[PDB]
Image: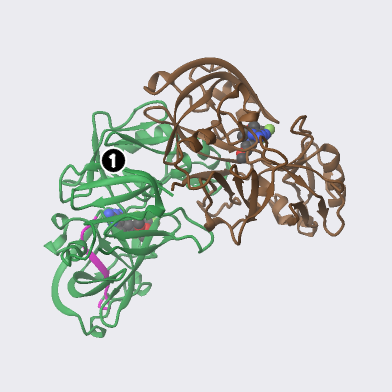
Chain colours: A green, B brown
């Protein structure tokens, strides 16, 4: 009978991270809570300073923790936008009043691109042990083993960005869901398969037409991804209907065209989940001379997880998301 | 025991709108939530494409909704600026986690001036049944009937526009208010009568002297109007005292001089509600080589409602507003 809310910071609507403590005394780290991966890692004090990303981030020093336990097994974590490498270490980790003995990665190789653009230091995988590298027990499995949570679930609220600092960037509840940050009722979709936060998606419509995901596709619900992503061929067609021009990494429209772009809907479990243009364009201007980025990207995720769409922070911002380990399902409700 | 919020989009500080769903399944429309009118309406699928506005808006297709019930009674809705016509239909409307069977207008006539400029598709009238054309029961009355709301009130937050954020454009709350977007406590002013969201104003001060509305006048609190307005005469005097001159269509001031302009105070229920020049000058720049318009316009509203001042989006931006149907009054508090 315990819940645990961790307050998240929202950087520019693209990064959402909260604080954890590792060691004794606690060394604090900004970390993304990430259902698209299953390992915990933070930068290490053994990371050569020729990696400038390690110069600009908090580094874990095992020599300052009395509760540290050595392992030393090498590990590499491959994310869709970048890679980190290092070795395994055990210590106590605090996540919102819960304390857990956890195996995590001390990262000694941390590419400047993209990690010099990271406001966060590391990542907390909220995914399953089946996708864990080195078969390291994920942190939420260790918390479940304590038997202190009311429900074996966790939930994500990602707020819109704000100019002031009185609005919360977001929130992860461990052991439940916060009714202050959603309205209406949860609508649940079973996982295709345990081991991945991935569900069946029946269709994707853009405007007055269902031009995408005909006959079906996959949808990984990914709190560690900034954007909604689809396959390269799915997105070239999505962005033809929008009128966006393919820039280097992102897509863009003329800023004045932003508000008139069509609704994009996502058919999940007998319910339509609809984003307006306000939800997926970074409306920085109304000028026909400036360019505005869309919060939708192309990403070709390889098997066995893909090929699939990924519903990242663009989607979760609109729909409060409950991840349910007990019944292997994902619930969505309108965020507030 | 229930509250229901809808996040709103701010377009250029002159349009504010959020999502509703009509039908089964729900079709998504952007609507202005409008205390200065009492009818719901969205564009119709039957709307001829000769009206260019219908080509560039979302259309309600009654054939694609299993909850739709027919009723072809005609109606014309006349606003200050534009005019639309159509016929009545019945269906379920989703307003932020609340569902309610509602009579609204499917619109088949939709002039380019001004509805081509409308970033919203339709309007949700939050006014009283007394000003409802066709005697149609307004949506808030139907929601009161299902008896789920905490209080018989609804509130409006309209945010300032910022080009360097993806900020909350605004927020309506049905059944209460959100203290995150105001400070202190509400002070209320009773309506003159039920049926119109219209209060007594005891004067409008420009700086020190109380130059206008000396012997009292009226004030519509209108969430569907973009500006504060007064009669052509009252605005003439106000603008002469501000040092503003009629450019061609609008009143302007040198952008650099904007900050020198005096406060404007609206005396409502024994308190002074004060906008600074930052609140009522659109400072697109501060250049001494450019002109800047004011968010206050002349508008001769005809009887029986007029002639009156109207406190539109300019005013609501400054003061979070709570519309209290139980007590027939309006509460203001400083927005944040
Ligand atoms: C968290 C680890 C993670 N987990 C899964 N499942 N997917 C991705 N893409 C990532 C990931 C990796 C690296 C990475 C990020 C995400 N994020 C997004 C954080 C999301 O917060 C919720 C970034 O912002 C950053 C700095 C990045 C910035 C950038 F401008 C372009 C990039 F390609 C990557 O670097
Ligand atoms: C909501 C319906 C409404 N309700 C009442 N009470 N008054 C007015 N004037 C209106 C109204 C009618 C039409 C109309 C608008 C408001 N608004 C303002 C939306 C306000 O959002 C908070 C418009 O922006 C628009 C497109 C318009 C653009 C323009 F450049 C000149 C116009 F005359 C009208 O067209």
Q: Is residue B234 above or below residue A36?
A: above
Give the residue displayed 76% in from the left and 33% down from the top.
B301
- The magenta stretch spans residue B99: no
Q: Is residue B129 visible?
A: yes
Residue toward you, B327 or B22: B327
Residue A335 at x, y percent in the picture: 40, 48
* Horizontal and vertical percent position of residue B284: 68, 50
Q: Where on the picture, by quarter, is residue B135?
A: top right
Residue A326 horizontal/vertical position (percent): 18, 52
Residue name at image x 83 percent, y 58 percent: B207
Q: Dot 1: within a 10 Å radius of its alpha carbon, few (fewer than 14), some, or many (20 or more) residues?
A: some
Locate residue A211: give its quadrant: top left
- x and y percent of residue B121 in the render? 54, 31
Figure quadrant of residue B304: top right
Mark 1, secondary structure of its residue: loop
Name the residue tied to disc 1: A231
* Nearer to me, B205 or A93: B205
């Amino acid at each position: 009978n315990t819940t645990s809310s961790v307050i998240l910071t929202n950087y520019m609507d693209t990064q959402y991270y909260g604080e954890i403590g590792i060691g004794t005394p606690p060394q604090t780290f900004k970390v993304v809570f990430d259902t698209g991966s299953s390992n915990v890692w933070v930068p290490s004090s053994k990371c050569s300073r020729l990696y400038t990303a390690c110069v600009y981030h908090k580094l874990f020093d095992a020599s300052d923790s009395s509760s540290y336990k050595h392992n030393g097994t090498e590990l590499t974590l491959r994310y869709s936008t970048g890679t980190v490498s290092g070795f395994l270490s055990q210590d106590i980790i605090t996540v919102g009043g819960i304390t857990v003995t956890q195996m995590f990665g001390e990262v000694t190789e941390m590419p400047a691109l993209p990690f010099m653009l990271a406001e966060f230091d590391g990542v907390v995988g909220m995914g399953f042990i089946e996708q864990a590298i080195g078969r390291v027990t994920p942190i939420f499995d260790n918390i479940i083993s304590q038997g202190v949570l009311k429900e074996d679930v966790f939930s994500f609220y990602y707020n819109r960005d704000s100019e002031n600092s009185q609005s919360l960037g977001g929130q992860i509840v461990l052991g439940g869901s916060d009714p202050q940050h959603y309205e209406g009722n949860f609508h649940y979709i079973n996982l295709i398969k345990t081991g991945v936060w991935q569900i069946q998606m029946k269709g994707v419509s853009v405007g007055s037409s269902t031009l995408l995901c005909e006959d079906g596709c996959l949808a990984l619900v990914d709190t560690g991804a900034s954007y909604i992503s689809g396959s390269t061929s799915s997105i070239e067609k999505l962005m033809e209907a929008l009128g966006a021009k393919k820039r280097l990494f992102d897509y863009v429209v003329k800023c004045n065209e932003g508000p008139t772009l069509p609704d994009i809907s996502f058919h999940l479990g007998g319910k339509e989940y609809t984003l307006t243009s306000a939800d997926y364009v970074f409306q920085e201007s109304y000028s026909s001379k400036k360019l505005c980025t869309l919060a939708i990207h192309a990403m070709d995720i390889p098997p066995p997880t893909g090929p699939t769409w990924a519903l990242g922070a663009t989607f979760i911002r609109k729909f409060y998301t409950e991840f349910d380990r007990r019944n292997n399902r994902i619930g969505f409700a309108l965020a507030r």
